Image (cartoon, coloured by chain):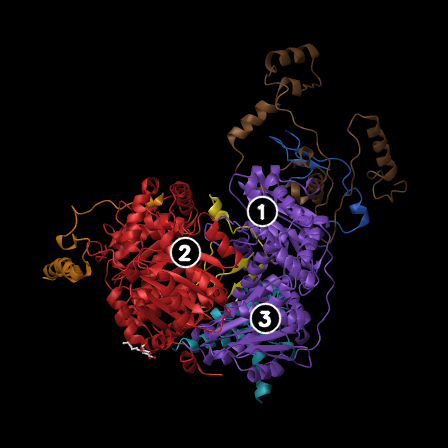
Chain colours: A blue, B yellow, C red, D cyan, E purple, F brown, G orange
Amino acid sequence: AAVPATSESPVSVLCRESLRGQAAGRPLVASVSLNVPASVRY
Amino acid sequence: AAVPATSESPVSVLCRESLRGQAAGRPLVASVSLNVPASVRY
Amino acid sequence: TATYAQALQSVPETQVSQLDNGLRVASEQSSQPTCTVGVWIDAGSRYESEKNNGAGYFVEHLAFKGTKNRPGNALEKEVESMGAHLNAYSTREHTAYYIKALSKDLPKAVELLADIVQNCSLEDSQIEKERDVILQELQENDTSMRDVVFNYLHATAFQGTPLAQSVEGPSENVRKLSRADLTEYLSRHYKAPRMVLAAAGGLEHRQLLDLAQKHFSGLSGTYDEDAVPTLSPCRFTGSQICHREDGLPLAHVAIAVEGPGWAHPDNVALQVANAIIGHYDCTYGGGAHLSSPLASIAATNKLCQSFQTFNICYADTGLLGAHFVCDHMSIDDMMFVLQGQWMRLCTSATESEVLRGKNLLRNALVSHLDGTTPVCEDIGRSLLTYGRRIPLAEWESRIAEVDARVVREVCSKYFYDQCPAVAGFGPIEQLPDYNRIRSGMF
Amino acid sequence: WLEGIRKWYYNAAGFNKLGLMRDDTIHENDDVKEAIRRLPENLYDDRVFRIKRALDLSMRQQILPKEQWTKYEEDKSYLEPYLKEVIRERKEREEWAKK
Amino acid sequence: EVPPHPQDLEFTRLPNGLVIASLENYAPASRIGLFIKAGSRYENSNNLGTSHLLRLASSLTTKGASSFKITRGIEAVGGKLSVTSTRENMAYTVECLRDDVDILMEFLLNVTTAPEFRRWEVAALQPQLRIDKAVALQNPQAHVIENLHAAAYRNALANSLYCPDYRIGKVTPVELHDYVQNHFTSARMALIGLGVSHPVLKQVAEQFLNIRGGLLSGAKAKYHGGEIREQNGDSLVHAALVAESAAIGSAEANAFSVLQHVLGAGPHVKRGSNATSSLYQAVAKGVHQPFDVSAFNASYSDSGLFGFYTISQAASAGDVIKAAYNQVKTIAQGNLSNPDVQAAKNKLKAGYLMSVESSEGFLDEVGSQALAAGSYTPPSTVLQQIDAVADADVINAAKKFVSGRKSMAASGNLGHTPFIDEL
Amino acid sequence: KAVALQNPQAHVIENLHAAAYRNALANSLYCPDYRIGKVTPVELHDYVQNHFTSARMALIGLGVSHPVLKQVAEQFLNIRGGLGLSGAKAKYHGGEIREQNGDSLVHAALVAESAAIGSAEANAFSVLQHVLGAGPHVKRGSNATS
Amino acid sequence: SHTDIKVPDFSDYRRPEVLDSTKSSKESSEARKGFSYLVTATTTVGVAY
Ligand SMILES: CCCCCCO[C@@H]1O[C@H](CO)[C@@H](O)[C@H](O)[C@H]1O
Ligand SMILES: CCCCCCO[C@@H]1O[C@H](CO)[C@@H](O)[C@H](O)[C@H]1O
């Protein structure tokens, strides 16, 4: 819709801090939109 | 070399007769040549 | 340790004898503890009419399914249990059945070939089972663009003659062929004077001959005089057959001019010429540096996935040319460079490229006759084609005498301003028009 | 005075005033183009910058401060080993092309 | 007629460990092969694919001959230069008329001891890795055998003969130089020749093949067991089930070789029903769609894999696989006729002799024996050893398979392809 | 698929499920490469008729009146073939899938079968997850309580 | 099967000298090329004039 995704796709990490949060913790979810960048969580 | 390979490469079976002999039976071997088509046995 | 010339004389001369019924028995003795022995017959689809076209191929499916002395899988079990291998092949002019086995097992091997060749069962139910096997093989072969294109090449180059026929035959024949057709065919063609019992390996000619006398003596040496199947020459027609199918990823093209026939001396120079142009495929390590101009251009410019020159011989004719596989946008370039190369050999072959061709040929000849099977086959087929085994030293003499002049003259004779036969299959919208192809011949 | 005239010539030629090294000024033929293609990243990137810097000075009809001029004694042939081999390879092919 | 051869094979081990073996057969052509302990098993996870690119680089520039010269010079004499790799060895072989062996030998020495691996030539070659691999992978068997080794081993023999996709374009000139320096050393090589004099061959090795250093080291291959499944939809499923058997050379290895022929190891008659193939007959009893099955036997220096390979319509994979397995089970339970073992031995013995009757087959065998056991064992002896295998040994090899931890790989529409724990 | 797969986590989670189950939950959220270009109109029509049925749906709404939402469902979401072509139990199998690709960083997941959602045991696993550590709470923190 | 493909009969279009499928067409090739090329040479002569 009106809101663009946090990160627009196209086709990093060098420290512990930037690495924390990268490990997955829940099952995967894939989203596709008409107006918004796709996403995959977990 | 002078002799062309059994099968020239480029980049199925419908009967039991044409299928006999397709099952592998020995470890794989890969060949590369200067003058002859490459091959992979087994 | 000898030189190349000295080694040619190292070759044991091939021994030939003939039984009263006219069967020829030939062998080449080595020290091999294994051997290959088989029967080569002057029979093939070129001998078939439209009505029984496919018969020989049908017989091939029956040959090892049981004999009167060894019904059903009996023959099979015997060959397997002694660790032997039984094979067969049928071309448009020759049929062969051969066994690979321990030399010590030669007597049994010769007995089995004899049993197969004279007492094959041809059981009605076996025949019906083989109909379906042959029909499935026809469907499989339809997926082989190379087999399709070469059968198409023969169909148009030799249109209206027995050589236009495929070896397998039309599907309708496979459905209708009867046991009677097969026996009539075998009756007229499987005669002692049209067969050669050949063997290569650790064996002696005297033992081979005694086994021949022992097992093939009753082989018919006379159909009579009303049968004696004789081949008429087959007219070659400059023509073109294009099977357009844009659904296939790569195009296959085969082009050829009429060749001389088996026994013609010209075949040596043509083989040298074909070795100069050579073969090629995307997996060759050479690339831009290959000696053949067609191969280097093809590799650097990515003109094809592959190509091969060929010299297919028949009794008094043949197909001399090349086959290539490429992208739909490269057909014209490939044809352009290929014909340019034939033209260049006709008018400008150099001594050095010709020596290279001669060296390639020498190496191909000797490396091919490596192992009992290839030598056994060379014996059987050569007696049928040349009437004798031509020794390596003779091939060497024939090769040595070829020079640039001979290559230009022989190429000019067969390629220069001659009508070719062309076959195309796949995304061939870009295959040049026949007139344009014909003008490329000069 | 040949070595004496050499340093004189080097400065008279003046490509050093634009910060160029002698090899940056060679006429590009096919042998040279192949040699440049063969250069390792760093030598290729440096060459690109020196040429770009020189083209920029040329457009402004200006030159670098004298302390930045390429020094005769420090100018070295970075291209020579590559070009010499490219030429050797072509000669070899040319020899083979004679029968 | 009366042949001159037959001479005997000559064998020599130099002080540096290099073996030189040859046979003057007086043939018009000669065959020389340099066998090396440099197969893919010697790659580690940091340089996977290196031996594959190396296999494709035999034609690149060397210190004594340019890339252009290697091709033109070998072609000028109608010769051949080829590289064959197995998980354990690499064999550089050349072919030519006997008067030109000095030319071929020189190129062979340059390729194996003086390669330059020029940065730009190496870069230009990377794309060939994709073409070479795609051509090989058109054969489902290649997919399955490669995955089977990856599933069976934790390392070494686990490595593929083909470069991993992620490594294509990444193999560096340095990795190639190091691979050659690490493994192309005298103690790891065997120079084999046919149609050549031994003194000459020997002298060549002494002067040009004295390469010191490198590593004769090499981590044992750790059999692990496991399964890799490649779903891809083909109407036909290709599958292989194996267990660890025996290292080549051992006596137990001969029993597995006999077991393989008892079971059925390839056709003997064109379009035949495989009357004497124990595995084939068992499957044929239960399945009526087209199919194929064969015992599978792979023997290596420090391990081996034995089992069976099957090809069937997707819906019948499980039926075919279980049937083949049950048939090996009956053998393990002692159900085996001495006649069948005799038939099997006949097949094995004839098959072996036929495999070395061509110059190519002979060279490979000598070369392989030279590296695996630094010696030459003639046919007579091989047949003896085969005869020496007892029915009990066969039954036991079969038991080992049945009770051994398995490894499996299948490709196709696997909806009905059983997992190891369902067998 | 390529966009999703730039995240190594996607690679790993997808392979973990393929390794854990024999079927069902084993399936990837992304189309297998070999199937790209092969999914037919018929397979799509069939998938919809088999699963988009009233007994397999829930219409949820925010900022809307329930009667209206309800009336909409009754008039337009009464889809027969309902209950549709349901599936089978997911068979936990266990196993491992290793994807060698050279990144400097290795991503790995180790699991065992736990409990179906809803069950009480599932809540214990959820608690165990937070005892162990389930994601950061402080920007650039040391995860003192993980 | 592709082996069911046969080239249609062209006897109605063939020059008479190549009507016999049991005879070599090479025996008449020079005569046939000579005829057509003669038409070409004469034309070129008339055009040069
Ligand atoms: C124009 C043809 C060139 C003449 C080549 C004949 O060559 C000769 O043929 C003999 C018969 O097999 C051989 O025994 C002999 O060694 C060989 O030199
Ligand atoms: C596919 C990898 C490249 C194969 C090595 C040959 O490399 C080629 O050698 C030629 C000399 O004859 C050079 O002129 C050319 O620039 C070079 O690319």
Residue type at mark 2?
A: Ala
Front residue of this view, candidates C174 and C367: C174
Q: Is residue C193 left or right of residue E397?
A: left
Instruction: Please provide percent x and percent y for residue E42.
Output: 68, 64
The residue at which mark 3 appears reads as E380
Front residue of this view, candidates C241 and F78: C241
Which label lies toward us, 3 or 1?
3
Q: Quadrant of the N terminus of chain G?
A: top left
Q: Quadrant of the C terminus of chain G?
A: bottom left
The image quarter containing residue A32 is top right
Task: Count up the numbered dots.
Answer: 3
Marks 3 and 1 sit apart, C-alpha to C-alpha, by 34 Å
Instruction: Please provide percent x and percent y for residue C140.
Output: 43, 45
The residue at which mark 2 appears reads as C88
Check contact, mark 3 vs mark 1: CB within 8 A. no
Q: Is residue C146 left or right of residue F67?
A: left
- Find numbered disc 3 in the image and state the secondary structure of the residue it sits on: helix
Q: Pointer 3: residues within 10 angstroms few (<14), some, or many (20+)?
A: few
- Callout 2: chain: C
Is any part of residue E55 visible from this angle? yes
- Find numbered disc 2 in the image and state the secondary structure of the residue it sits on: strand
The residue at which mark 1 appears reads as E310
Is any part of residue E118 visible from this angle? no
Residue type at mark 1?
A: Thr
Residue at 40%, 65% (x, y): give it: C211
Q: Indicate whether C305 appears above or below E33.
A: above
